[PDB]
Image 1 (cartoon, each protein chain N blue to C red):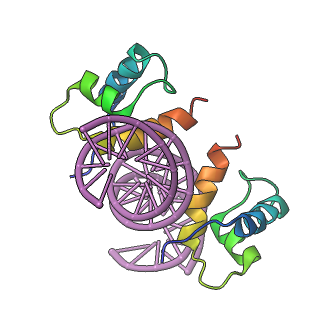
Image 2 (tube, chains in turn blue, brown, purple, red; image 1 turned 45 degrees about the horizontal axis):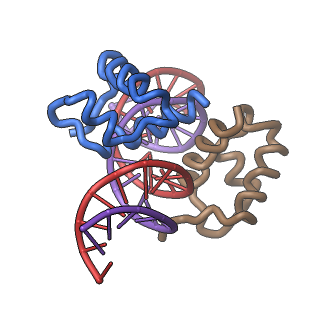
Length: 57
Length: 57
DNA sequence: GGTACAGTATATACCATAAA
DNA sequence: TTTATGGTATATACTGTACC
């Protein structure tokens, strides 16, 4: 299937990234392990963090 | 093949986008037709303009 | 009701580096 | 010399809309 970043999933992702101390500091694997979401791969998080990083700073 | 945005190709792409009056105004097809580069598809330009747009404004 | 396109989201491939 | 990872570049899929 193709992942959809629903506004909940994204809010999870953000809280995660904040805990990790901002988008720049945060790591894919780190975000992954904090979210603990069934079926979410590292590759899902990696791509999305890449966007999140650019649409921020 | 997989396209590589060599610093020349990119300089072409930019001049194009400028002629078209900035990244926001510019269109994939428009940039395409101004560059007139053998083997360059609209899909190449589309993706790259998407990046150019975010790493600018 | 089918193109052709723009805009956007997501995925995938590349490239370097560290650790073993 | 593999494996795992992060960063990054590029590609591919989705969604709407205008035109015909």
